Amino acid sequence: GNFSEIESQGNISLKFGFLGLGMGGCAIAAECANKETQIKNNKYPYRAILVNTNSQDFNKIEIKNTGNVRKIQLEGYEQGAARNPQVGEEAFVKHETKIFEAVKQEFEDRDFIWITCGLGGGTGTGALLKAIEMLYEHDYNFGLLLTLPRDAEALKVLENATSRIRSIAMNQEAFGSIVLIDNAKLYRKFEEENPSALANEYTSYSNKYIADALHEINLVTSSFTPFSDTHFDASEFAQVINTPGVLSLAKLELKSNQLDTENPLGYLTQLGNALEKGVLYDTEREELESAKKSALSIVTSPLRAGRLYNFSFLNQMENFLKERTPYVDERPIAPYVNKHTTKKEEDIVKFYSVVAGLPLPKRVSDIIDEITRIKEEREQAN
Ligand SMILES: Nc1nc2c(ncn2[C@@H]2O[C@H](COP(=O)(O)OP(=O)(O)O)[C@@H](O)[C@H]2O)c(=O)[nH]1
């Protein structure tokens, strides 16, 4: 995930802060906060506060971005493998004053905060609702960056996740977007693109993959030259990220010759598949249909832009999004020119979309059925 070229000539739309809770949430938050960029006068664009109980692992969470990443240790509530949310909850409440003082100072210059948490654990999951109340009570603009557990994590972790996800959705109107991450999906993605990969490379891969997906859309929305008057800029991006409900990201890269405007079915089908098989989780038409907001940006070279962004293409794209998110407040189709595209990448056309205000995905229901299976077979066994 090297965005050096783009960063040296671009910028990020929003100054994100990450409030990590628990091991996984802190690992993801740290991965994002430690990102180094080639952005003018902004080597380290992100900040983070990592809240977790003491442990060797938590001590192990590196930290490159100095000063912009602070660890807050939940003294006295180390939980071990108890996987008990009630304890995580008590921990957060007990240390709330210390935590908020840290949040207050570190996030003063932030535009938006991501409460980052791996659903299923004790500390993170347990502290989640309290953390949300804290940011809400102090009027921060914030959203949730959450992972859903793999089936192998078993019963307790799945119930822990199911419990919070349910409560989150019920109270979703109280805050911004919920960027869901399906660990099962990403685990599979890893195996497939790295068949000969070993288990020791997954965690790093998934955390970098997540951080890169968020940073990339943050970059794309403020680093290129708009071809027209329709934009998906920092302002619009903020509008979308602040929309309640689940948020889905998609990205498709095609070679210029695979994008036929006289025979659009081919590339429109690929775009449709990219939107459903999203970056962080998998969605479907039924879910997309109820989107509250959506935006799609297209980026290509000076060489290709002029010939691509014609009436036919733009109209086909307008139609495409209209069929996918029919009831959206606004769905801009925003073509961009990357004026500094290399000769080597001259033919590439990139598509980026963000869909917001979505319902919980199918993976949440599959987890419920996995929990249901286990409990019912346990009864039959009895
Ligand atoms: N993507 C990702 N997910 C993680 C990571 N660590 C843990 N998780 C997930 O988050 C869930 C909770 O684990 P953890 O954060 O360690 O528990 P906690 O410290 O008690 O909150 C697990 O069930 C995993 O699915 C990580 O480094 N990356």
Image (cartoon, rainbow, N blue to C red):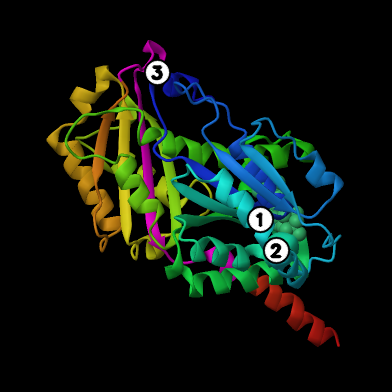
Q: Is residue 168 left or right of residue 375?
A: left
| Image location of residue 207, percent across then percent down | 64, 41
The CA distance from mark 2 to mark 3 is 48 Å
Where, quadrant-wise, is the N terminus in this rendering? Answer: top right
Q: Where does label 2 land, which residue? A: 92
Which badge, 2 or 1, is on the more N-terminal residue?
Answer: 2
Residues marked 2 and 1 touching at CB (< 8 Å): yes
The CA distance from mark 1 to mark 3 is 46 Å
Q: Where does label 1 land, which residue? A: 99
Element type at mark 2: helix
Quadrant position of residue 133: bottom right
Is the CB of mark 3 within 8 Å of ligand 1? no
Magenta stretch holds residue 259: no
Element type at mark 1: helix
Which of the two discs, 2 and 3, sits closer to the camera?
2
Three-letter amino acid code of the residue under disc 2:
Phe
Q: Where does label 3 land, which residue? A: 345
Q: Which residues are magenta?
A: 339-366
Three-letter amino acid code of the residue under disc 1:
Ile
Q: Is residue 373 above or below residue 61?
A: below
Q: Is residue 203 above or below residue 124?
A: above
Quadrant position of residue 68: top right
| Image location of residue 138, percent across then percent down | 50, 61
Mark 2 surroundings: few (<14), some (14-19) or many (≥20) residues within 10 A: many
The CA distance from mark 2 to mark 1 is 8 Å
